[PDB]
Amino acid sequence: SNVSNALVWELTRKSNCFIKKNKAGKKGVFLCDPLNVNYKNTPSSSGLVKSNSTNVTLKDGKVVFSVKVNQHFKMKNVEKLLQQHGSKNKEKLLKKYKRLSKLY
Amino acid sequence: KSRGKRSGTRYKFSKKFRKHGECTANKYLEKLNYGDYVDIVCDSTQQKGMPFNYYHGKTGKIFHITKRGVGVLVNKRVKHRIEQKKVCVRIEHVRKSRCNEDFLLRKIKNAELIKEAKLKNEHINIKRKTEGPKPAAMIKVPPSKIITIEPLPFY
Amino acid sequence: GIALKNVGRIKKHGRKHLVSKNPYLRLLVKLYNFLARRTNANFNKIIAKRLIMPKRYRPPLSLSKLQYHMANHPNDIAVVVGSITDDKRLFSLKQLKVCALRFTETARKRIEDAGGECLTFDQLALKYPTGKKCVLLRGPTKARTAEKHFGKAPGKPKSKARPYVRSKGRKFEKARGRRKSRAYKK
Amino acid sequence: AVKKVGKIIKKRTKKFTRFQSNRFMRVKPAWRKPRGIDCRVRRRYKGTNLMPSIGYGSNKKTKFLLPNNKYKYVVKNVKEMEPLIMNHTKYCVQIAHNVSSKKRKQIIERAKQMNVSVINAKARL
Amino acid sequence: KKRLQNKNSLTNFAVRCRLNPAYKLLRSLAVLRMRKSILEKSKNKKEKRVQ
Amino acid sequence: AAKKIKTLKLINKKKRNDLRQRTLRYEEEYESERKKIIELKREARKNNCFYREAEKKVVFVIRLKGVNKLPPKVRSVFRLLRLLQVHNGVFVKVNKATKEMLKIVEPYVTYGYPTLSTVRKLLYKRGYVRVGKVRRYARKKIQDNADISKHLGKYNVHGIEDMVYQLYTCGPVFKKVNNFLWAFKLKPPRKGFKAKRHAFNEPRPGDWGNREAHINELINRMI
Amino acid sequence: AKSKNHTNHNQNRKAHKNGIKKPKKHKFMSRKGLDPNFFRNQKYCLKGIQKKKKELKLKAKQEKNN
Amino acid sequence: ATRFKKNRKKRGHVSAGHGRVGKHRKHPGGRGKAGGLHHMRINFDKYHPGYFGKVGMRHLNLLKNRTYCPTINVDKLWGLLPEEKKKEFSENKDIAPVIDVTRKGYFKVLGNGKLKHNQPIVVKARYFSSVAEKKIKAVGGQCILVA
RNA sequence: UUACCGAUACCAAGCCAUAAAAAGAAGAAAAAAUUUUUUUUUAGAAUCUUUUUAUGAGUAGAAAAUCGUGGGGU
RNA sequence: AUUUCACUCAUAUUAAAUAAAAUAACUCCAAGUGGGCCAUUUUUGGUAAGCAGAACUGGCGAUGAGGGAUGCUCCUAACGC
RNA sequence: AUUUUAAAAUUAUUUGAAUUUUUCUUCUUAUAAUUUAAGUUGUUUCUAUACAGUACUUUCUUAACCCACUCGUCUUGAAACACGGACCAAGGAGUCUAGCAAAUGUGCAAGUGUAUAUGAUUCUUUAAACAUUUUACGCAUAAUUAAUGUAAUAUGUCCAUUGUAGAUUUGUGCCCCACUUUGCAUACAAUACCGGUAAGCAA
Ligand SMILES: O[C@H](c1cc(C(F)(F)F)nc2c(C(F)(F)F)cccc12)[C@@H]1CCCCN1
Ligand SMILES: [Mg+2]
Ligand SMILES: [Mg+2]
Ligand SMILES: [Mg+2]
Ligand SMILES: [Mg+2]
Ligand SMILES: [Mg+2]
Ligand SMILES: [Mg+2]
Ligand SMILES: [Mg+2]
Ligand SMILES: [Mg+2]
Ligand SMILES: [Mg+2]
Ligand SMILES: [Mg+2]
Ligand SMILES: [Mg+2]
Ligand SMILES: [Mg+2]
Ligand SMILES: [Mg+2]
Ligand SMILES: [Mg+2]
Ligand SMILES: [Mg+2]
Ligand SMILES: [Mg+2]
Ligand SMILES: [Mg+2]
Ligand SMILES: [Mg+2]
Ligand SMILES: [Mg+2]
């Protein structure tokens, strides 16, 4: 009753510990959130503000699937996971996962 | 150096040629109300109630009326700002304005016009039509009356 | 060049954004701004403006005053864009429905007792997004002690402004220029 | 003059050097705005150094784009590299000047995996 | 609405038409006037002289 | 919604139709008036009497002098007119007060009787208009009739043609139209001025006089 | 030292920047030091009127009550 | 804090904001109150009218206590009771609350404000203003002088 | 009498800032390949984004936004 | 004279124009400034002065740009890139 | 991601008219397309079948055309035959406290501030943080008078003084309108009443 998403955003629009902004080349403010699909500093994409998020991260070596209440998992498998707990965004996530896979 | 109440007033208070004497007895019968506009024209025949040099000519609303005293709200431009000044005068210097009554007449006429319009349901313009462009005219002039002109030689 | 006034740019003399960093308050202002922009019902805009305003221009509204205001129309909801304080001077409190930015605890308690309703701004919005059957009330702004020093300065004739003094009594600004007997007066 | 390349317009390639920075050693080129009466620069006499002004600024749209068309992003660590996985066509990595060689190499490797351009890959190469 | 060019009316026929619909008719009339052969004009001269 | 849209379209079409007819009427009038003038002249010639043409009702005023080194009264007059830049042109309804104002700023402006074609040209190539809530105007070029049909819809003057007509001869709604029109930001003359210091009526080459019949020419030159 | 002791130059200009501020012209000017006796009479009249109004209101209230 | 001080904002300008022609010299107008009644008389007149001169009687040994008498208006008297108790009192026209105004830390009762009609109040205090007393009585209450 | 040259003034167009004004809490577009892959994006940060128009001299001075240095908590 | 009722006064051309008239009022808090100088015109003292002293307005001062070869003030015109 | 739409215009059709008898004659009934709408796209080269070259980018370098007077400074006015400055590096100037002020932020709000000081299961940080005894004082809530002092409608009605403009509302015919309806803040007054002082009376 005292805490809501908008409020949270307001609190942490500036003062985050995931916000990293390029000092050289001023345009660009990134969120290093464990639940950010696109690493933008927007309340409509950030994991801290959004109640339900299903981001794919790298964490420590192996690619990890994160769900929001917080869950952690591990292409077909990823798709299945998405299908299970998930409510365009999915496509984006899939794309991201592909990219992640490429990295070792 | 010398700024008295009647400084630079050799001509402003001086009565006009062949119009000295005193203020006429009928001038005191001029009726005034709480809202009338009034010109302050100083008759230096009556030294009592003499307003300051500046207010001679300038008009203003009457805000106060006494036995023989008339209080007038006169706008004075003071450097950066025009301010209201309450000048307590006598009747001898106070004269009723004329513009106000010009306005009044117009208003009266306008009312009549309005009434007339109503009588017949019509769109009659009331606003004063200022001197605009002259309409097309055909002026009949005989060749006998048209007198030709040429610049005059020097002498 | 162009012979203009202040050249081109149109002066706006008022607040633009709240300087305040109060997250809740910011949220509220955002909400009301949104309301203003979508539904130009004026009321919303006014509310937004009030929210934006500084603390002096949200003077506290006293419960008694509120009651007085409500005295004509009942059941409609008085909205106060500031704090509402209680008044020991009042004996009875009617069934009031009041939306405020802030209730002092005691005032709130009083309202509750009256069997009334205390609404926050969000609640009000939810209830009445067009502000139907609402009545905007303000506290007495120029009743503030600061304002008593303003206007024509004490020294100018017929001015009713409080001089800035140390204390009060004979020894303190009550002689020359304050009585016919010591040079002048006022 | 103006330096068009792509749609990228640069209005003023020349640096604005301090007045008289070329006359006394003690005065560095770093722009300082002249004050005080009789400046000549302040007064904008024909033939002197120009004063930087807001008119010179680049279009809001292409501003911090480099010749590559990518905003430069400084990278100290793999973790930081990661925010640009979904942005390889818009931000280009520069590895911090103070990174040790092994770490730099690692970063470079990561970049290649990501398809992200590195603007300073050759340091300590 | 995003500002586009500002299109010369006097030239850009379509724009002109949009501005003033009757204009087309006027243009047509003008064209027709232009069309008529010079012989007729010459003939008319005599008439004019007479008048 | 679709139905509503259709209705709107229909209305627009109707308006356009109405506009066209109006335009045609105006055209008919213009020629007719000219013809009548000629006839009148002929009549005058025939009979010893003279025919004076009606004072041209409107006057087009173009600035000459700059912002600097100008009296306060003159500046005020300029402001009133809506002439603020060195080559700002505007239409002014010739009156008594207006005339006086013009006289007061005589040495700083060139003015005269614009003629219809010239006016039309001005409207077309240089006609910019104020689109927005009062005191926040935004200078927008006309191009479309729907841009002016919002503000001048109450006064039965939809379309540029109507506006032009109004400008040409002081109709029931001219002042409003003038107000709506942004001050004509004109070029310098393509053949150049004679001399901005001297008067047009001066025997030597000049400008700032009342060039009643050559104003149009000037406008054309600097269009 | 000899100095420019007086000038009214630029003063006008200065005045004109904020413009010659006209009097605010309030509808109800304070009738304090203005014509006595009459003003007290006026006051009395006003009071009477107020009283009458109050009485009327009371009557209305009574009627409502029944 | 220093970082948001204006001087820091003026740092590259020559006169530090204190004027080029009229410099910033130490104590120009004089020291402290200075020429109050001489070169600064006008200011005194306009902002501090009755500053100069002494008025009235001396009072060599004051002792503010002797004269201490905190006031309360009747308007605030019923407020001095808790809400529930107040309600009870309102309900029961039969019983009237006594109030020890001294016990609540006030020495004088003044009469600014209405009191609820009919409701009798018993007021204990050291001082009363005539009007306050009258108000109390009108409502069927009494003032009982205390010390 | 023309013609021409000629400003940081004027006009037309762009871009920058300032001011104001409109207005804003869900979705596949194209190309390259050979019906399916690949290449780009797939926006919604309220002092924010999109667009619009006007405007831009400046000492004394005032304000705002930034920038940097020594240390502190994070 | 005040108050309450009545009837009834042009109004979208808006009680004559015209008006980038609310960029207005008003309140507060302060800064700098309070040596000025020049030009046309009116002008006082002075033989006169690039002299001293004034009036209306514009400038310079705070201001560059084009012209006046050159110039703080003359003319053109005030300046984002 | 629906005002790059809608219309205009144009092309080929289809129905009805018109006096401007016209291969651009106009309106209009319907349908497709196109651009004169609805701010530049296309074709062919070239760089180039290159990893840097002599090309391309850019830094520096002189040239050259045109311009450009030593900065700071006080001054009506400085390039001045006004002063300060040979050069360079480091240091080098509106600060801190007391009380007051307005501004704004914040908490609480007829109160507020826990002052000293105590208390603790407080003791690297702990010189802070927490807690406040199982009617302290400040400022404010009342003013005014030299003063003994006196102290704000006035118990008919818990009601909340009267106007004129005034936000918001309530209705009538979702912003303007023209009425009603309520009358915030505030401006402008008017009254009451309180303290003082006149004046009139006066135990
Ligand atoms: O205004 C919606 C919205 C909703 C919500 C939610 F309801 F989840 F809290 N939160 C939003 C937030 C949020 F508060 F930060 F989450 C920001 C912006 C829009 C939000 C937008 C609507 C457009 C799509 C993104 N959410
Ligand atoms: Mg004389
Ligand atoms: Mg100088
Ligand atoms: Mg110098
Ligand atoms: Mg020439
Ligand atoms: Mg400065
Ligand atoms: Mg100095
Ligand atoms: Mg500037
Ligand atoms: Mg000095
Ligand atoms: Mg100076
Ligand atoms: Mg100049
Ligand atoms: Mg010469
Ligand atoms: Mg001249
Ligand atoms: Mg040279
Ligand atoms: Mg000197
Ligand atoms: Mg010296
Ligand atoms: Mg030396
Ligand atoms: Mg030295
Ligand atoms: Mg140093
Ligand atoms: Mg404060």
Image (tube, coloured by chain):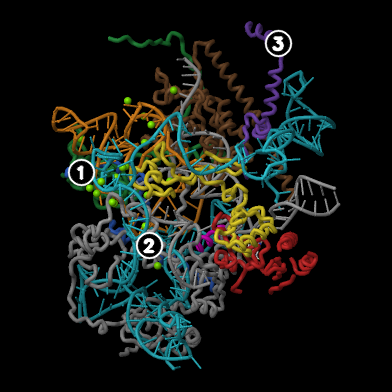
Chain colours: A red, B green, D yellow, E purple, F brown, G blue, J orange, K cyan
Asked if the residues shown at circle 2 and circle 3 are in contact, with their CB atoms under 8 angstroms apart, the answer is no
Given the image, on which type of amino acid does mark 1 rest? Asn
Q: Secondary structure at mark 2?
A: helix
2 vs 1, front mark: 1
**Residue F21 placement: quadrant:** top right
Spatial CA span between label 3 and label 1: 88 Å
| Image mark count | 3
- The image shows residue H120 at horizontal and vertical percentages of 42, 85
Instruction: Tell me the chief SS of the magenta region.
Output: helix
Label 1's element?
A: loop
Report the residue at 17% width, 75% height from top.
Answer: H57
At a point 39% along the width and 11% down the height, the residue shown is B149
Of the four image quadrants, the one with ligand 10 is top left
Picture disc at residue E40: 3
Determine if residue A43 is in view: yes
Percent x, y of residue K101 = 34, 65
Real-space CA distance between mark 2 and mark 1, rounded to the nearest whole angstrom = 57 Å
Residue H39 picture location, percent across and down: 20, 57
Q: Secondary structure at mark 3?
A: helix
Magenta segment boundaries in residue numbering: C40-52
The chain to which mark 1 is attached is G
> Do the residues bearing badges 3 and 1 touch, measured as CB atoms within 8 Å?
no
- In this rendering, position of residue A49 left or right of residue B94: right
Ligand 20 under 8 Å from disc 2 Cβ: no
Task: Identify the mark at residue G5; answer none if there is no mark.
Answer: 1
Disc 2 designates what residue? G46
- Closer-to-camera residue (B11/B62): B11
- Residue F123 lies in what quarter of the image? top right
